[PDB]
Amino acid sequence: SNAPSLISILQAIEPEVVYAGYDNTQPDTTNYLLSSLNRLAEKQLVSVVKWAKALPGFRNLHLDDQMTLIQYSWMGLMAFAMGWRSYKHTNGQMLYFAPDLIFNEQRMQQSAMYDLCQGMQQISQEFVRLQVTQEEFLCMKALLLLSTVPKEGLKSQASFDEMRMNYIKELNRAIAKKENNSAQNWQRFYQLTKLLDSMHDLVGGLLQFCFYTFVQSQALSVEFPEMLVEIISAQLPKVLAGMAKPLLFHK
Ligand SMILES: CC#C[C@]1(O)CC[C@H]2[C@@H]3CCC4=CC(=O)CCC4=C3[C@@H](c3ccc(N(C)C)cc3)C[C@@]21C
Ligand SMILES: CC#C[C@]1(O)CC[C@H]2[C@@H]3CCC4=CC(=O)CCC4=C3[C@@H](c3ccc(N(C)C)cc3)C[C@@]21C
Ligand SMILES: CC(=O)[C@H]1CC[C@H]2[C@@H]3CCC4=CC(=O)CC[C@]4(C)[C@H]3CC[C@]12C
Image (cartoon, rainbow, N blue to C red; front, side, top):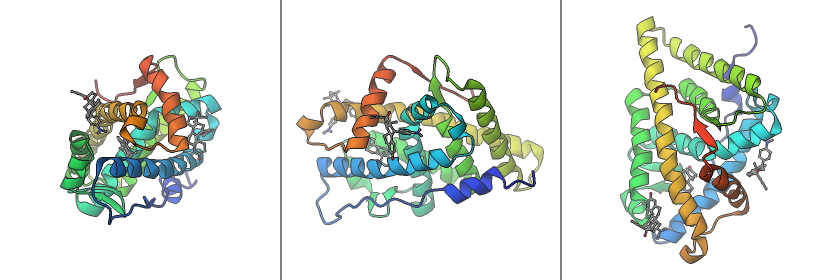
């Protein structure tokens, strides 16, 4: 309580932005865009793992819970942070994958996943509409890691549930700082948690494309780096068996 707030810790451990290493002089083509996003995903994946290990409460989970949460959440976390970066850097008009890999209309079209790009942009436009604050975002991003679990339950169910309640309490703390009335805070919590819930449907779409391009990678000439291959190969069978379920705030 005089302890450093959870928010101050989340601010301290928030990763720095990852560069794609993209050559912007190349023409916009499907396999160079998709292979480059996968190379970016590989670098963001090490960032995410490092961030997750520092997240207060996370290391108290069983190691199999930790790995499972990561497998189930990586796409959503990266998609959610992209919504944030697109909001802060382009007011939701473009997809800010990295400072050196920004998608405009032409690149979204050449990516072969135009509709999904639009999905991702709609998330960014909801950040813009709510004017999400940095403190809200960081709490929401933690909660997103804790929002897809095994149907069978986790090995550390009590520790997980306590951790989830602590991050929800911190999101409400971040909201109440603006010093609005209580009813306004309720509304804000509702809007932010709707935004979180809306990630699940987007992610399902993103997963469908990713899994397809993964299975067809040779024929499409779309490169998947080693760690991405590992996490997709692990996740794909569990999703197929329907082992994961979303934890929704709203029915
Ligand atoms: C209708 C139909 C059809 C299909 O021809 C079979 C699977 C489709 C694929 C599935 C999974 C899929 C998911 C999407 O969300 C957008 C499109 C999509 C497709 C299609 C597609 C077309 C081109 C690529 N490239 C070049 C990487 C990738 C996917 C159309 C696909 C191939
Ligand atoms: C082979 C294999 C495998 C996997 O089970 C799927 C994805 C792996 C992930 C890749 C992406 C990845 C990137 C890293 O930087 C270190 C580890 C790592 C992993 C794995 C992993 C192991 C332990 C944790 N903890 C305890 C937080 C987190 C991640 C091993 C993963 C999950
Ligand atoms: C090549 C491919 O299948 C695409 C479809 C969805 C794409 C991901 C969409 C979410 C995303 C956000 C980032 O900021 C890193 C790149 C990623 C992680 C994208 C990597 C390439 C993906 C996985």
